[PDB]
Amino acid sequence: GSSGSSGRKKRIPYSKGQLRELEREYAANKFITKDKRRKISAATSLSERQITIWFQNRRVKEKKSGPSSG
């Protein structure tokens, strides 16, 4: 709570309600367009850039050498 904590703060961003739309859109297409990207920003209330960064990390995750690295 205050002290004696290894460090479980500043964890992964994007709430379940936000990632819910991202994950779904991703499953449909690894890459979105200005259109979809704009819609998601209206639902998840995220920035066109933020959403992109997430979609990229999702793909790159299986591109670089490190499937189980984190």
Image (cartoon, rainbow, N blue to C red):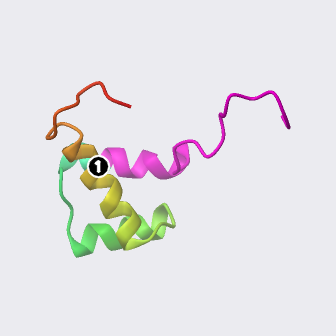
Closest to the observer, 66 or 49: 66
Left or right, residue 50 beside residue 55: right
- Crowding at mark 1 (Cα within 10 Å: few <14, some 14-19, many 20+): few
- The image position of residue 30, as x and y in percent, is 18, 50
Kindly identify which residue carries mark 1.
57
Does the magenta portion include 21?
Answer: yes
Does the magenta portion include 30?
Answer: no
By secondary structure, the bulk of the magenta-drawn segment is best described as: loop
Give the residue displayed 44% in from the left and 47% down from the top. 19
Left or right, residue 70 beside residue 44: left
- The image position of residue 8, as x and y in percent, is 65, 34
Left or right, residue 36 beside residue 8: left
Give the residue displayed 44% in from the left and 71% down from the top. 47
Left or right, residue 64 beside residue 35: left
Q: What SS does tag 1 mark?
A: helix
Toward the top, the furthest residue is 68
Q: The C terminus lies in which quarter of the figure?
A: top left
Q: The N terminus lies in which quarter of the figure?
A: top right
- The image position of residue 52, as x and y in percent, is 30, 63
Vertical side of 25 occupied by 4: above or below: above
Specify start and end residues of the magenta stretch as a single range: 1-24
Vertical side of 38 occupied by 64: above or below: above
Closest to the observer, 37 or 52: 52
Which residue type carries mark 1? Asn
Vertical side of 24 occupied by 32: above or below: below
